[PDB]
Image (tube, rainbow, N blue to C red):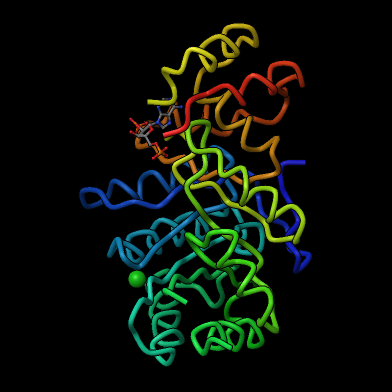
Length: 257
Ligand SMILES: Nc1ncnc2c1ncn2[C@@H]1O[C@H](COP(=O)(O)O)[C@@H](O)[C@H]1OP(=O)(O)O
Ligand SMILES: [Cl-]
């Protein structure tokens, strides 16, 4: 498919637009271009200070009938380290107001780490303000600690994952536990890796396409970021072809960062 299914049963489109900060309008324009090209998944973070701009882009898309709210998968994330658990629902409330949404499909949190911070997340899940809840940057050990005590297990662990940083341990642990791994920075320069250039030539694809497809074939969603409209489109062209097993195996020889 063009999606994975989370432990909640919800579908998460395999490709999303990644989150970042840029000059005024740049991110909104990317969101708009992405969704027009077929993206159904947008990753956001209040830390970038741009969720109102993204909300303006989403609002345009919806008003224009490009997509319905229900066919979008919107994610936001909170970095809550050393803040109160009570701040969590307030931040979600703010993100919803800025994005002009009634619910998030996914809300992710980081804190140092029964944890009351996670408790606050569970309540938002119970309420349907966050249809799925997860974590960002949790190692296998920390993700396992959380799984051992949570009432609602994390749906997602969003981490840096790419051919130069393959997260092999965490990938195995997510697969065994049913937590879905979303790869941020899925292009890392790993696009100059000769193994990737070679596979790209053998398959008649770009280096980025190969790198993205590799992650998808490990069962991971990917969050490529681009301000270029053509690269936005190419970053979605990861579905109607695959990397064969013999070429997929060569990824094991790439040097890790
Ligand atoms: N299809 C692509 N081919 C090459 N570079 C890309 C592609 N898509 C995005 N990028 C670039 O990758 C970087 C983001 O990588 P990551 O997601 O791993 O952090 C950006 O500098 C972005 O530049 P650009 O915005 O000019 O497209
Ligand atoms: Cl934050």
